[PDB]
Length: 211
Ligand SMILES: Nc1ncnc2c1ncn2[C@@H]1O[C@H](COP(=O)(O)OP(=O)(O)OP(=O)(O)OP(=O)(O)OP(=O)(O)OC[C@H]2O[C@@H](n3cnc4c(N)ncnc43)[C@H](O)[C@@H]2O)[C@@H](O)[C@H]1O
Ligand SMILES: [Mg+2]
Image 1 (cartoon, rainbow, N blue to C red):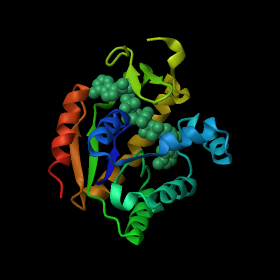
Image 2: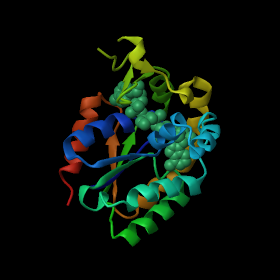
Image 3: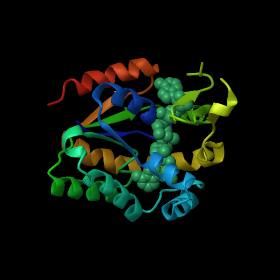
């Protein structure tokens, strides 16, 4: 399957991606993960990305498109399918993606659009804790771990003032992107305001209705 998953920050893209990958075995491509990996390994791209990510701002499109395209162009994806998560995040990236996909002879089969009440998102991100090895996320109230602190951390961009900036930035950029793909008949709206397993149940029905 060739899929996009999108939603505002904290809407549960990563949480749902993990469950999607477990069942459908698509390749998870998360720009967020790629940036954070670059940072932790102190690559050049990591140093530049940090200055944006620490502020809750979008990383420039050219760097973002390039790394996505690099991933999309590799030999795996043709036969395994992917789940693009956190990209495209600007309409420019959407156009870049579409061109890139056409060149490669790859077609999007669906967009999973997780809709969540924006009033829920500050709390989702403020309570997030992250398992180090897997990057699996938990929530101290809504989805607590079975704890041991050495195994967890909190994302730098999850401090409330950064979250508030992230939300503003992405509420403005997300509307033209969803419309772009809805116009192509590719958008599936998911009720994100449920338990994690109920959200997944909805997504699973969508994915087993494709193709
Ligand atoms: N294409 C791009 N172009 C330019 N710049 C880019 C870019 N991509 C990334 N960047 C830059 O990198 C930065 C980070 O990007 P990125 O990592 O992609 O962040 P994001 O899109 O804001 O998404 P998050 O990981 O913060 O939220 P999520 O929806 O995956 O939530 P989760 O599943 O963990 O869940 C959140 C919390 O809620 C809990 N939770 C999940 N579901 C539920 C539920 N139903 N009920 C209750 N709690 C829930 C979870 O346990 C967790 O605690 C960007 O801000 C930007 O600077
Ligand atoms: Mg995520």
